[PDB]
Amino acid sequence: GLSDGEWQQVLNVWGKVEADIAGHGQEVLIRLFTGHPETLEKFDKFKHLKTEAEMKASEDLKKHGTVVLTALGGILKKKGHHEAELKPLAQSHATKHKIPIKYLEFISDAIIHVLHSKHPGDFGADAQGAMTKALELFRNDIAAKYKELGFQ
Ligand code: HEM
Image 1 (cartoon, helix red, strand yellow):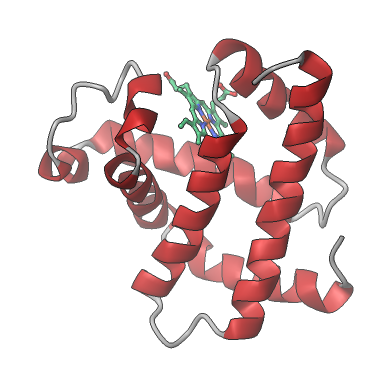
Image 2 (cartoon, protein in one colour):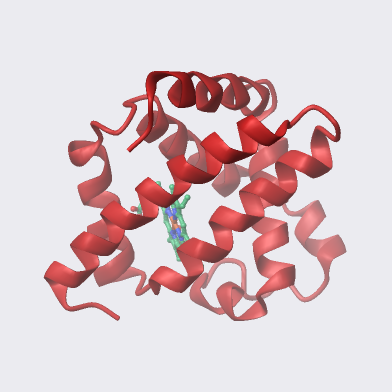
């Protein structure tokens, strides 16, 4: 649950992402894959990537980064009223991709890391607080659907 002022911070930060969605999406996935190499094994189309240089050179990884952040941005713009947008993603990630909630924690922290890396000194403590709360809400509502499905 976020206040109006917190949502305003989230959507202000998101403007930074929308200026370069592919570059942000690429770096988020690279941070996930290099920090948590077990996550790469869930992607049949990226498991061939052995080095970060190959990851950086992969145009399909940048494409998928655009898909991921476009979906997340659509959810964030609903300011919590995201049941219709979130349900299909919860279902596909639990039942088809088999993504444990832990990996959603990993990618949430990766987003925070990338924002500081690309905007050092321009991602203030209030903005980090609000973005963190928004990603916690996203993860918590996914977790509720995971529990319904019995997925661990
Ligand atoms: C912010 C969190 C995430 C968002 C918004 C997101 C979004 C998406 C979307 C929109 C798709 C394509 C449609 C679909 O299959 O539902 C997708 C596919 C997929 N996601 Fe995610 N995802 C997220 C996190 C993760 C994480 C953490 C993992 C694994 C560590 C993951 C694994 C996958 C896989 C394996 C696919 C299929 C890729 C393919 O072969 O095309 N997702 N995701």
